[PDB]
Figure 1 (cartoon, protein in one colour):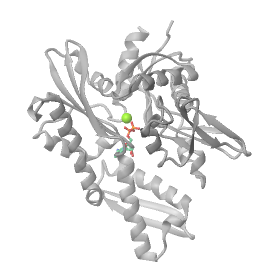
Figure 2 (cartoon, protein in one colour):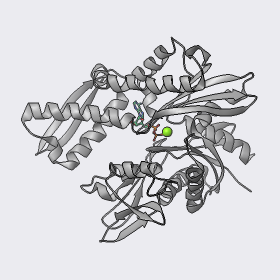
Figure 3 (tube, helix red, strand yellow):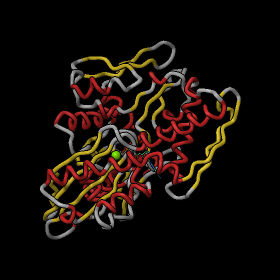
Figure 4 (spheres, helix red, strand yellow):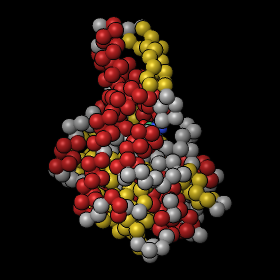
Length: 382
Ligand SMILES: Nc1ncnc2c1ncn2[C@@H]1O[C@H](COP(=O)(O)OP(=O)(O)O)[C@@H](O)[C@H]1O
Ligand SMILES: [Mg+2]
């Protein structure tokens, strides 16, 4: 008895959970009211473990005791060159244990803990499970979980193992771009079609060329950039306001961490607002040395600050086409995935790359992966 199976997007930066109820997919909001949840862990001084928004939102001078981006490490060996490169950029300690890159943090009272990447991912799945259980009013035991198309055997198995730790029987692992296609019902079509999935997220960018024939998907080619997404657009805005503040006041903002943390949170909020309005205000009381911060950002300035990065996303699309032996006119469906595809300019540039062809529309792009997982979960719940 699998009960109500949940569909989970276990994301590098943001995760999402959905279920099939009363004849449709329902994307479930967490206890902070959000339909996506940061893949983030932290600790209080008392040694309480925070997960999700509360973890990411906790003001700290000790980023070395937060954990995030565990998906970059999951199912890999310590000596994997990808791991050895990624640990340069992660503020928390990673140590070799049982051949793997375990995460070592202080959690309160001088207590040290060491966690496998799949134990961190298990904490995130637990939070997703709790989110679904609160919505459903009952326990959940089974899940469909998505992974990037490029995940190998160890990465898939380690994702299943994270489920096991979280008390979730991972019944099916499905590829993220495929899950998005399923969300749009592209599996339920006749003839053979070429689908280009453009997935621009928080820290990661994935482009995938899928074919669909008689209900069966094949991932023909993949590309992208493992360190390009909305976090980078935020940093460009940060640099803009840090330089302006120095020019204005003479002071170097970066000397104070919690200040940088406050500006980052407000910059991210502003960026999101600018996907649906043309100006946003950034305001922070007691920003730096007792002085308040108050500035505006226009959509045009946001675009100007990131135009080169926005344009760089086309190169991996051109590469998957060449690797697929396809031209632009061979693409039958374009699917936008990832939170950063909410950016109007990103939509515009993809459409222009495809000579005016409209993408699929109607599912929030940061939810589309979980949506498709939930579709499959619906069938499995019966
Ligand atoms: N309305 C929006 N406008 C611009 N960016 C957004 C919007 N909503 C979410 N984002 C960005 O999407 C990114 C997260 O993408 P998502 O696909 O949810 O994460 P992941 O890459 O971890 O799967 C973040 O940088 C977030 O700031
Ligand atoms: Mg994603």
